[PDB]
Amino acid sequence: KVFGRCELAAAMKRHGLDNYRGYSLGNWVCAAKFESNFNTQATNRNTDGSTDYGILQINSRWWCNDGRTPGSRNLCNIPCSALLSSDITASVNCAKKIVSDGNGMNAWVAWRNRCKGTDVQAWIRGCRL
Ligand SMILES: [Cl-]
Ligand code: NA
Image (cartoon, rainbow, N blue to C red):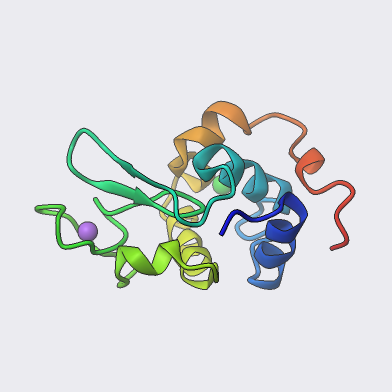
């Protein structure tokens, strides 16, 4: 599924991401735009053989099991496929654990490089929320 900007904003809010660990909803929508371009089926293979999955490009190195990342953890205790679903629940629950790990949204390199310190509330403005 390729979410609308406002559609994703609404889903992330109903799943409790607005101000989760102090990050306003715009931060989460900005992160999804540059991670996946709002495509739930996005994947990207890393040079280390791990894979990033779904709307927030969550990595098999630590967070989910795909059966093809030797020596990896699965700290979200989920199959990495679960993160490609048209329904964002598993991705939001996993992302809550990630952002609580110590480095907050810096865990998403694209958020640190492209969202952090910008007017992120621009990503939710005009949205019925
Ligand atoms: Cl933080
Ligand atoms: Na893994």
